[PDB]
Amino acid sequence: KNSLAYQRMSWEALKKSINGLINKVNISNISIIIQELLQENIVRGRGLLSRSVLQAQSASPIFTHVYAALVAIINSKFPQIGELILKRLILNFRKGYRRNDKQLCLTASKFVAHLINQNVAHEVLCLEMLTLLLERPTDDSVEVAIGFLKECGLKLTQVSPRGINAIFERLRNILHESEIDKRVQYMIEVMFAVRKDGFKDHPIILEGLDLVEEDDQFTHMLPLEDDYNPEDVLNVFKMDPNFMENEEKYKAIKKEILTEINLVS
Amino acid sequence: PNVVFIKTEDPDLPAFYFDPLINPISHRHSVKSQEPLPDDDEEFELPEFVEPFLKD
Amino acid sequence: KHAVQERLAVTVCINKIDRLILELKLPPTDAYYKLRHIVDEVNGLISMY
């Protein structure tokens, strides 16, 4: 009826606008686009919010950091949101890897590296990802770990240099006592290049991708082989008998959250 | 021959301890090598009185 | 190169090994790494000539 048509128009126009803002979010529009994603109730459609974030970080190797800044904004505030996104990107990374999808694995691993540098992803899962990447390194998984480390070699080494030294030992032995070719040879060389360069080509987060304060953040730890879930069926809407109750509640949450003497001488 | 003896920061990390200061080895080559490698499964075995010279 | 072009016997003595231990402060695994490296470099180069 009227309430039904209202929930349907809500889902439709809301999701379309939130996906617009997902692909629109900028760095000179980081807080603006995040506050527009809040001016719309992004948690009412939390599933398709995780879905827009995931879609951006997957199909954009160059807007993964931007989708990540949005994720950090919404995740220090509603950690479960970036949390669903994190479990999702873990699903997509294990998808790409365990199905031998280089591009899918790379997309999800860039998303997880952005999360680890933003400090929404914990270091033990990054360690497990590097380790399952370097277990039997061939061209693909060697480049996968090295590409992850191209951006996330900084955060792991700054919170736990143990992981950096471990990565150096493992990479050096797996590529220096084993039968790999110029691909993984020059790949190890590139890894050492970033290392010795002191992560100067790729720090943690460029200006505007980390502004949330020291302990005001949320780094939730949901690991790789832990049987996590996507919980992404929330990308399809659902009827609401408590639509008005939860609407007042979530709108209240978004309201509560926002001489001439030199001459002469 | 220039001497390279690297000052430590703390006493803590071990005597031998690869520090960032040294450049990361990362020795690269072709298919590295193979040897006149005396495979086991013919046989060899260590009479266990000789454990590693000073592991204690 | 000169020894290859005049076909002599080829001996190699790696020397000055305290420079890995007291001077370099290199843990043993990466010590072995460097040793293997010197060996593989000189060997690949003799393969060059």
Image (cartoon, rainbow, N blue to C red):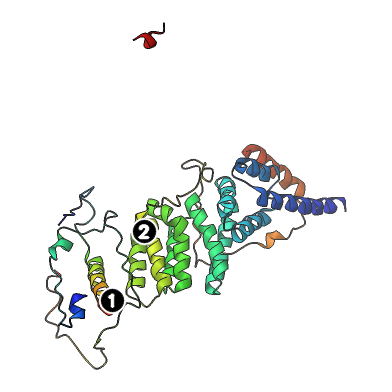
Residue A100 versus residue B1 in the image, above or below = below
Percent position of residue A142, x then y: 44, 69
Q: Residue at x 15, y 61 (%)?
A: C19
Closer mark to the observer between disc 2 and disc 1: 1
Determine the image quadrant of residue B42. bottom left
Q: Position of residue A177 (x, y in %)?
A: 32, 75
Q: Which mark is residue A164?
A: 2
User: Is label 1 in a helix, a strand or a loop?
Assistant: helix
Residue A241 visible, this angle: no
Observer-nearest of C43 and A6: C43
Relative to A72, does residue B45 appear above or below in the rendering? Answer: below
Amino acid at dot 1: Gly
Q: Check the image and report above or below for A243 versus A252.
A: below
Q: Which residue bears the numbered disc 1? A: C44
Q: How many marks?
A: 2
The residues tagged by marks 2 and 1 sit, at their Cα atoms, a distance apart of 30 Å
Q: The residue under label 2 is which amino acid type? A: Ile
**Residue A162 appears in the rendering:** yes
Q: Position of residue A79 (x, y in %)?
A: 56, 50
The answer to whether residue A60 is above or below residue A42 is below
Q: Residue at left 70%, top 59%?
A: A235
Taking B10 as reference, is A94 left or right? right
Q: Residue furthest bottom?
A: B42
Q: Nearer the viewer, residue B12 or A83?
A: B12
